[PDB]
Length: 145
Image (cartoon, rainbow, N blue to C red; front, top):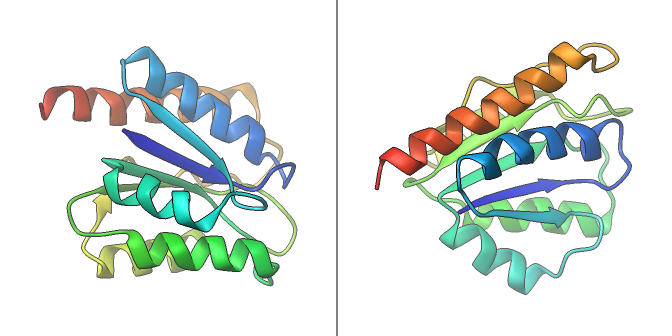
């Protein structure tokens, strides 16, 4: 399955993450959504290790205690047999896509789709790209089985 993690009400995370999620479920992949601001670390761990793919919205530079712990827990559990889909949440002071991408590739992950770079208010175009990215990731998984 694919785990989609993001911050509730941070930038356009809910909306971009939902658009990617919509693309993903249409292909028949089971999507597991998690709110980094409040999810339980213990389950997050199991959720990540069994995930065939991980989709993460960019988290702000100075993340809080819960989300830094959540973030660290994903990195700690992510491994080399899975894909990473990154999308810019367009929040306030958030971590650059490139930085996260480096971390994941070093753990041995490949990209689930091209990073979704949003540098302005997400338009319908951007949401279509999120949906298409979810669809593509889904079909890539539906075929690798």
